[PDB]
Image: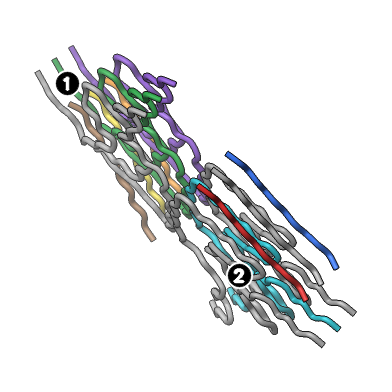
Chain colours: A green, C purple, E cyan, G red, I blue, J orange, K yellow, L brown
Amino acid sequence: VLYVGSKTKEGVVHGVATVAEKTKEQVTNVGGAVVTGVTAVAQKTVEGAGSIAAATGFVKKDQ
Amino acid sequence: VLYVGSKTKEGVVHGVATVAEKTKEQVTNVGGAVVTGVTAVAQKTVEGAGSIAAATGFVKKDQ
Amino acid sequence: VLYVGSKTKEGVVHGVATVAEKTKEQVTNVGGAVVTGVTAVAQKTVEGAGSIAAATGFVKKDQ
Amino acid sequence: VLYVGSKTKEGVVHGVATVAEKTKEQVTNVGGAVVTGVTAVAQKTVEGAGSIAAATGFVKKDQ
Amino acid sequence: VLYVGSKTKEGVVHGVATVAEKTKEQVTNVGGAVVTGVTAVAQKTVEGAGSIAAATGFVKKDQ
Amino acid sequence: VLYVGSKTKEGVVHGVATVAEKTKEQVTNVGGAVVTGVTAVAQKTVEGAGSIAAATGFVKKDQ
Amino acid sequence: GVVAAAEKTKQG
Amino acid sequence: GVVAAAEKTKQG
Amino acid sequence: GVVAAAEKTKQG
Amino acid sequence: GVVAAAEKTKQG
Amino acid sequence: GVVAAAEKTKQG
Amino acid sequence: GVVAAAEKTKQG
């Protein structure tokens, strides 16, 4: 019984319940970005960036 | 029974309940960014940035 | 019984329930990006970026 | 467009979210009645009694 | 378009989300009644009683 | 378009999400009744009683 | 007549 | 008459 | 008459 | 250069 | 340069 | 340069 660096928990999601009742959902984009409905998401990243729900219209970089 | 660096918890979500009742949801963007409905999200990042619900219209950088 | 670097948990999702009742979902994009309905997603990344629900309209970079 | 006795609503429950985090629940009865944890319950009754969460130890009625 | 006795709603449950995290649940009864965990229940009754979560230890009725 | 006694709804359950995380559930009864975990239940009854989650220890009725 | 009973002894 | 009973002894 | 009974002894 | 376009006409 | 466009006409 | 545009005409 030493428990060195053990029984850890990092980047965990559990026990999620969700109900979504809609009559008319309508997404309409022109030259852009849309992110809708992200749920029950977990991750762990080492030596690097971590992004889960990102949106970007555009990254225009000319000469 | 030493418990060195053990039984930890970092970046955890648990026990979430959600109800969303809509009659008409309508998203409409033109040359932009929209993020709607992010829920039950967890993460851990080491040596790097961490972003969960980010939006950016555009990153225009010319010559 | 030493438990060195053992019994760990990193990038885990469990116990998720979801109900989505819609009458008319309509997505319509022109020259853009749409991400809808991401759920029950987990990952672990070592020495590199980690992205789960990302959207980008466009990455136009001319000469 | 007359709408006689229409578009009614009687005995309805909707849009309920609940989280219950316990470490040790213990029920122990001897010759009695226990009701625990009633939620999201609806009903309609015509010409008769309506009971939802009732408890009764005993109804002893001898000769 | 008359809508006589139409578009009604009686005894309805919808849009319910629930999370229950326990470490040790223990029920123990001796000669009794236990009701635990009733959820998302609906009914309609005509010319008669309506009971949803009822408990009764005993109904002893001798000669 | 008359809609007489039409488009009705009576005894309906819809859109239910549930998560139950336990480590040790233990039920133990001796000469009794136990009802645990009733969910997403609907019914309609005409000219008669309606019971959904009922418990009764015993109905002893001697001579 | 009916009878119900319980008992929980724990030394230590 | 009916009879119900339970018992849980645990030394230690 | 009916009879029900239970018993759980555990030394240690 | 790239071009995208959409159009939805509905009389009635 | 890029171009995006949409149009939704509905008489009635 | 980039261009985005939308238009929604509805008589009635």
E7 lies above or below E63? above
Question: Which chain does the numbered disc 1 sit on?
Answer: A
Q: Which residue is mark 2?
A: E11
The amino acid type, in three-letter code, at marker 2 is Gly
The answer to which image quadrant residue G4 occupies is bottom right
Quadrant position of the N terminus of chain A in the picture:
top left
Residue located 39% across and 34% down the image = A12
> Residue C17 versus residue A10: which sits nearer the camera?
A10
Q: What numbered label is drawn on residue E58?
A: none
Q: What residue occupies the far top of the structure in this picture?
A: C63
Residue located 47% across and 48% down the image = E21
Left or right: K8 as drawn, with respect to G2: left
Could you say where residue C34 lies in the image, as x and y percent from the top left? 37, 34
Tell whether label 2 touches label 1 (CB within 8 Å): no
Can you see residue E20?
yes
Q: Secondary structure at mark 1?
A: loop
Question: Which chain does the numbered disc 2 sit on?
Answer: E
Q: Which residue is mark 1?
A: A61
C43 lies above or below E10? above
Could you say where residue C18 lies in the image, as x and y percent from the top left? 51, 45
The answer to which image quadrant residue A43 occupies is top left
Could you say where residue C47 lies in the image, as x and y percent from the top left? 29, 14
Left or right: G12 as drawn, with respect to J2: right
> Residue A8 versus residue A26: which sits nearer the camera?
A8
Q: Secondary structure at mark 2?
A: strand
Quadrant position of the C terminus of chain A in the picture:
top left
Q: Tell me if mark 1 has few (under 14), some (14-19) or many (20+) residues whose alpha carbon lies within 10 angstroms of its own.
A: some
The amino acid type, in three-letter code, at marker 1 is Lys
Q: How many marks?
A: 2
Q: Are the numbered discs 1 and 2 placed on the same chain, yes or no?
A: no
Q: CA distance from mark 1 to mark 2?
A: 59 Å
